[PDB]
Image: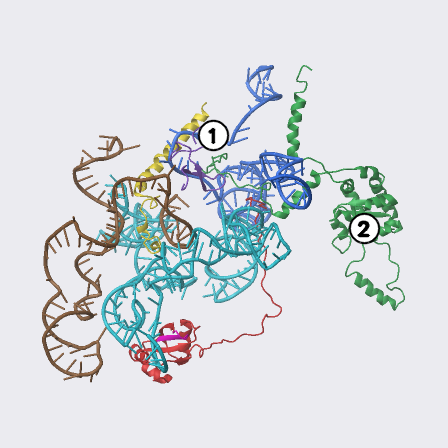
Chain colours: A green, B purple, C yellow, D red, E cyan, F brown, G blue
Amino acid sequence: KVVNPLFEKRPKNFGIGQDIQPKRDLTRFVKWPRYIRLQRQRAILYKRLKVPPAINQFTQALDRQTATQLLKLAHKYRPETKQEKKQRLLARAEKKAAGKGDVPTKRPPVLRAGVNTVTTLVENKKAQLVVIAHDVDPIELVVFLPALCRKMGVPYCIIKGKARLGRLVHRKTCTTVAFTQVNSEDKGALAKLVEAIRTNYNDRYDEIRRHWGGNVLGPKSVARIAKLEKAKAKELATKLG
Amino acid sequence: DPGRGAPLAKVVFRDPYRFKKRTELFIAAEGIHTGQFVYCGKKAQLNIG
Amino acid sequence: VRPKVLMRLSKTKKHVSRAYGGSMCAKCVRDRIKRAFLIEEQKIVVKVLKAQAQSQK
Amino acid sequence: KKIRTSPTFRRPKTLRLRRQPKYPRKSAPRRNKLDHYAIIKFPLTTESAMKKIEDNNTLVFIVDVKANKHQIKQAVKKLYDIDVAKVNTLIRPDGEKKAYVRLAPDYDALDVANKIGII
RNA sequence: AACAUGGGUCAGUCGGUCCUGAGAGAUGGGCGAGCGCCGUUCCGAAGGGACGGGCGAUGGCCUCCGUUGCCCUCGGCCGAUCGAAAGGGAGUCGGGUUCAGAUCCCCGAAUCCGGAGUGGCGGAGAUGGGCGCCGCGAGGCGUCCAGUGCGGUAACGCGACC
RNA sequence: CGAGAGAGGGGCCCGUGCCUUGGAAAGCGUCGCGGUUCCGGCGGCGUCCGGUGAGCUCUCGCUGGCCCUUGAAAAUCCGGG
RNA sequence: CCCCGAGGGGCUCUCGCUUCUGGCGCCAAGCGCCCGGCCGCGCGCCGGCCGGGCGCGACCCGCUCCGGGGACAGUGCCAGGU
């Protein structure tokens, strides 16, 4: 990059037969392995057809910052994980001789994870907030759940990721969680988010259940029809009519 | 080409993605010879073979 | 010689002293090596001429 | 990065380990079933063998059918402490490997033979 | 040529093993109640390799060479395997010897490949050109600069010639 | 055969033929003497000079004829850019 | 072409512009941004000394590899005819 009387560009000119094309990052053409092809095809199918209403309800998930308030709320409420369970229980065994604590004693309100437990307390109407992971392997696991919450007026929300609900315990995933009651000092902070949630997921159950999805035609065919629509819009009124 | 009276033409093409040659065997159109340059593709205008 | 004998034959004995040779035949050694020039240099120069022609409409 | 140059997806090259067995699969070493005394079974004594001894300075042993020329050479040399010039064998139609062993030029076959016991 | 008792077949160089032919036949896949059958690149994440750079771990004498792990960088898997004592397949000949064995044993004279990565020896690389000074000379002192062969117009030669 | 005929002057490829190194000491044929048996015993003289050919058999090479047949593959080794 | 004042806007095709020759084409040039070690300073992203990265060169975006058919071939089970 200095002036040397001998440095010379040797410019290249690509183009057919001029000089062989150079290797460049291809990611559109490669023969992907079978399972990767499978994931691509399924993801594309779920748009290229129409999902039913009870499946399309699973795509209007929460706003990220709202979910962040929900989670920061939960992280003061997560249940007892490993190496905490053991230490608390051992200390409680030692408090037995001091008459101040055993296994039977008050536990402040905590989360309720499993689907069976969550549905039980929903149908007993002991739930004040329900969260739902949106990507669950067999969707029939919780396809019914929003309808149940609509039947019994229990606030419920559709969050992204089962992984987050997993992180909300020591486990790896949890289909749902639910607050039954919370510490009063946090009751108001709960209720504000509760109202924000129920404004969007409960009062419009009509449009949710009426909703349809997918049916979105691929960009190739979008352009292919755009050609003829442009042609007809452009040359309309062709006859003196 | 044994067992066929339509003799094959063996053609050397430069491979426009690497440094090598591909050698194909077409059905020799009548009247072509050794040492001809054969043009193949969308814009190669009318010539024999 | 038999192509397996070449593992012991002297280097010099297995090729002409010329460049781009020793993999030819007498007619190649002469006329192919001349042809590789009488074509090559003429063509590069004519490419220069026709490039000047493309610049001069 | 350098995420692609070829259209052919190729299996990654993972990291592979080596056996760290908890228990050795078997128990213990299996000793040699042939030390030197099984490679060298017994010498041979025939007229067409003492001719070899007194003319070609060569010994004629009989060895277990599975015994290399190298093995025969080393085992006889270790036994009789006698250096061997070369060894050639064969499989008699019986099934013993008769082994002709050309002693080294520095040794007297008629001396080492009557050392060993043969006539 | 029977019967009984003894003895005989020595290979780097002679063949097999090495490779592939017509074929044969495996796992991917498929069909099938099923032992299995179909199929040989077709529905497969098919390269366990490496010249080299960087880091680590070392052994000598970690002088500076040898070894290993790690990080890159490069590669068509362009199809496991078998299939030819007549095809392809580098390298041994002469004399002598036996109650039977010889391109094998003995004598003599050569060979091909692989080793020596501690270069074992010699030869080539390549040993100068210009300089100012003590010198008839010779070389010399210090400078600098070139040195990955030579010859013939040609075919190609000379002992090797990154 | 004007894409270089004849004409001279050269280069290479093969090279089993001939010279010599192997090498006469070996081999052979003859005359002889011992060990007289076992001897790869020891002494002599020799193994020389031409021709012939549509001969036969191998092998090497040039050039032709034939086909609506075109005449195996890889392992391997090598030359150049 | 509609426009011009010598600058150029609006509109259509365009293209990787590879054809006389039994050659030649790879493992990047150049430029731009970055900093690593040495000397002349110990103010050093100062000059001079050594050695490397990214970006451009090679544009961006994307839902199927690209084409060809297609809700018919076809397969599965029944049904008539041969």
Chain letter behind tag 2: A
Of residues G46 and A75, the one drawn nearer to the viewer in this rendering:
A75
Q: Say which residue label 2 marks.
A: A177
Q: Of circles 1 and 2, which is in front?
A: 1
- Indicate the quadrant containing the C terminus of chain D: top left, top right, bottom left or bottom right: bottom left
Of residues B38 and A98, the one drawn nearer to the viewer in this rendering:
B38
Percent from the top left, x then y, of residue G43? Answer: 60, 47
Q: At 36% across and 78% down in the image, what residue appears?
A: D60
Picture layout, residue D23 above or below residue C12? below
Whether residue A5 is visible to the viewer of this picture, yes or no, is no
Q: At 40% across and 32% down in the image, what residue appears?
A: B30
Judge left or right: residue E126 versus residue B25: left
Judge left or right: residue A233 versus residue D96: right
Whether residue C51 is visible to the viewer of this picture, yes or no, is yes
Q: Quadrant of residue F57 in the image?
A: bottom left
Of residues G38 and D102, the one drawn nearer to the viewer in this rendering:
D102
Percent from the top left, x then y, of residue E53? Answer: 51, 52
Disc 1, disc 2: CB below 8 Å? no
In magenta, the rendered stretch is D92-101
Q: Say which residue label 1 marks.
A: B44
Percent from the top left, x then y, of residue G78? Answer: 69, 44
Three-letter code for the amino acid on which mark 2 is drawn: Val
Q: Which mark is residue A114?
A: none
Judge left or right: residue A172 versus residue F2: right
Q: Quadrant of residue A83 in the image?
A: bottom right
Magenta stretch containing residue D83, yes or no? Answer: no
Three-letter code for the amino acid on which mark 1 is drawn: Ala
Magenta stretch containing residue D95, yes or no? Answer: yes
- Identify the element where label 2 is drawn: strand
User: Could you confirm whether marks 1 and 2 are on the same chain?
Assistant: no
